[PDB]
Image (cartoon, rainbow, N blue to C red; front, side, top):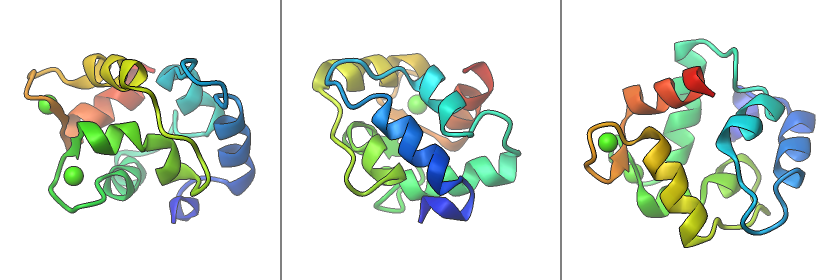
Length: 109
Ligand SMILES: [Ca+2]
Ligand SMILES: [Ca+2]
């Protein structure tokens, strides 16, 4: 699970910090969860967990389930939160997040 690269206590704190619907901010979430400061190889492990269907990209519906990839009991994002998250990282405008795009989201957070 995500604990292969992140700490169980950081996951719990970061997910709880965004329990309120509509409040997700990936930048603060990446800080709280301890993903900021991870090497490219460890970021790739996070990406692969979020890419549930092995497509090589995090599609929009996989982004909506981002919190569940960190913690199984996390809530889904709203469509508004998902669209904002996608817009923050989808630099080629294809509607999904690739590996390099995701690494850049971690770097810019
Ligand atoms: Ca996918
Ligand atoms: Ca893209």
